[PDB]
Amino acid sequence: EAEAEFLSRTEGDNCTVFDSQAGFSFDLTPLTKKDAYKVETDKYEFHINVCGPVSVGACPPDSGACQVSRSDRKSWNLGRSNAKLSYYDGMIQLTYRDGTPYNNEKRTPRATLITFLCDRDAGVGFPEYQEEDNSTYNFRWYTSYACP
């Protein structure tokens, strides 16, 4: 399986994205936090940051997204520091680096894909953990900064 069929992806380098189709430029830099964001589940938390690295005490500073089992205290790397914002027709998505791969034959990196959704008036935004399934962890982020 391939990561997207590639239909309208505008990929930036730093955590700012300008999409030529959409004609709008979005800065997701205020969304970057040193303290970072934490999504909590029953037995795990996902701590992620938009752009750069994540400063969690569960994973090395070179990580941009880190999860830790609040149950076992196991922690995994969900991608090393990166700032690649991609604008996908419809929503903005951020893809993180290889970090730490599972244990599969494909050597598949546990990565974080943050899908930014339009929320007309919210604030900086709150991410929510949706589905790890595509070997990458997808979070939805409701932020006004992702909406025109």
Image (spheres, helix red, strand yellow):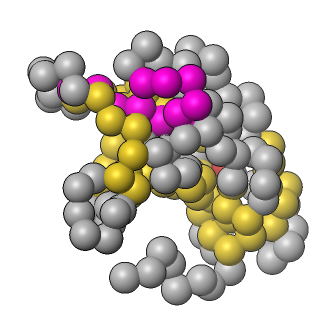
Q: Which residues are magenta?
A: 59-69
Residue displayed at 81% across by 67% down: 19
Q: Quadrant of residue 64?
A: top right
Instruction: Check the picture and name the quadrant holding the C terminus.
Output: bottom right
Total residue callouts: 0
Residue displayed at 48% across by 36% down: 65
**Per the image, is 95 magenta?**
no
Name the side, left or right, on which 38 lies relative to 63: left
Q: Is residue 58 above or below residue 76?
A: above
Image x and y of residue 14, in percent: 79, 47
Residue displayed at 76% across by 34% down: 29
Instruction: Check the picture and name the quadrant holding the N terminus.
Output: bottom left
For residue 49, say whether it is visible. no
Residue displayed at 22% across by 26% down: 74
Q: Quadrant of residue 11?
A: bottom right
Residue nearest the viewer, comparing 87 with 102: 102
Image x and y of residue 31, in percent: 66, 31
**Per the image, is 67 magenta?**
yes
Q: Is residue 116 above or below residue 135?
A: above
Name the side, left or right, on which 48 lies relative to 50: left
Residue nearest the viewer, comparing 29 with 121: 29
Image x and y of residue 89, in percent: 64, 74
For residue 108, say whether it is visible. yes
Name the side, left or right, on which 67 lies relative to 148: left
Q: Is residue 128 above or below residue 133?
A: above
